[PDB]
Structure formats: C-alpha cells, structure tokens
Image (cartoon, rainbow, N blue to C red):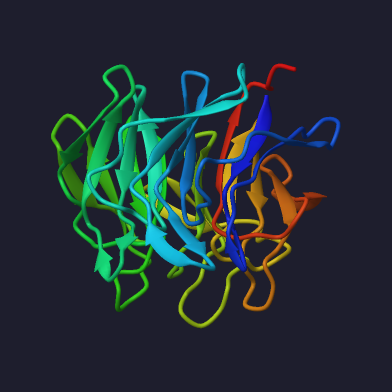
Length: 289
C-alpha cells in the first residue's frame, strides 16, 4: 500500500497524482487528474481512490468543482463519477459503510453547511441533514461509524467547534470543542482517537496537534509537528499519521512529517517532488506495471 496525493496548489491548481512508498522512499508519478484541482479531499472505497470537490485556479479562470473522480491503481486510469449537488472548494469527506460523505466547503461566496452522501454501487449522490455550522476548510473523520466535522471557517469566524453526524438518525450534534481554533487543519482517525493537526486560526499557521477521545469526550494536545502548516493533507498508513505539504504563511511546503503514536514523536520522512497545499490524500494498494 502507498500514500497517494492528488491535486494541490502552487501558483495554480495542480493535476499531479503521485504515490509515496514509506518503505523504499520513492514517489511514483501516475495518471494526471482530468482537471487541475486544489482544496479537494481524497478517500478510498473498495480499493479505488476518489478525488472529491475542490477548485480549479488556473491562469485563465477560477471555478469551484462539484466533481467526483475515481482512480483505479490496477489500470492507472481515472474515470468520472456523478457529481455532487453543488461545488465544494475546501471540502472534507469521510467514508461510512462504503459510502462517501461530502461535508461543507465553499462555492464562490456560499459557505456550505450542507452534506451529501455518495453510493458507489449506484453512482449516485443524495443530500443528508445539514451541519449545525457552515464550515469551509473543515476536517472530517469517521469513528465507529459516526462522522465528525472539526473546525473550519464559517465565512466570518474560524472555528474550534466540532460536531458529530449519526447516519441512522440523520442528525448532527455538537460535541466538545477543540482547544484551538483551526481552519484547514488535517483531521484523521488513528487507533481510536480523532487527530487534528495544524491549520490556521486567523493569525498564525499552527504546528499544534490535539486528539479526541470519545470515551472521555475530551481533546488533549500531544506532540506538535515540526513545521506549522495550513491546508495540509493527512492520512494514516500502518499505524502512523503522515502530513503532506501545506502553507506556512510564506512557502508552499514539500515537507512530509510522520507521527509515531507509540513514542508521541514527529519526524520528517520525505519531501514531495514539489511543494503544494490543498491536496487530497489517501492510502491504497500499489499500482500495476
């Protein structure tokens, strides 16, 4: 299994799909996305990689994207899927029961609180209950088949609140807020905790990391990253967290850091082939040759 990064931003939105091998350190260059996009999210269902939402910032135009596209590592080919009901730049997504939930994001000046669910076996999207909060640059994770939306920006204020979606009640409930306001943080599940790493609080890019224990409904700050960063990508591979790129207020980072939960330590393990922010990241089997 490899860490795949899709899209991103450096001066303009990007079409790169590259896959990192934590063992042998290589970055594999794979088929370009059909459209350059930044602010998208990535996920894997079955063994297929999905690129969801985002925005195409190009020298000739700037369009948010409702697109859903699917990458098959066995063919090294992208195929479109049915699109979401609206464009969603700076989206978060999570997977429950083999279905993809698309959460928040922006379309122009619209800041979504809406949420919709994709069923791959029908290739179709349906709207679900909207969040309590409009959230762009929202971090999303799934724990025990409940869907969490963490932080973001509501168009006026950046957020430390978090809320939780119950699929079978079709309702959102506020949970305990994070210690730190964060939009564009990296949010993932590791072991049985929700991690929120980095992001932006409206004054500084952040290197802090905190984690939510559902048993105690509390957020605790752990080992902070080496490099402050907003709009980073994040994923879990073999029991460790990987954060990719982002923006530190000056530079589009190529740094990749890795969190070992057993030692509560971060280390820099590689650099992307070029710095970028706003990627979609996810883990799936290695391609065929």
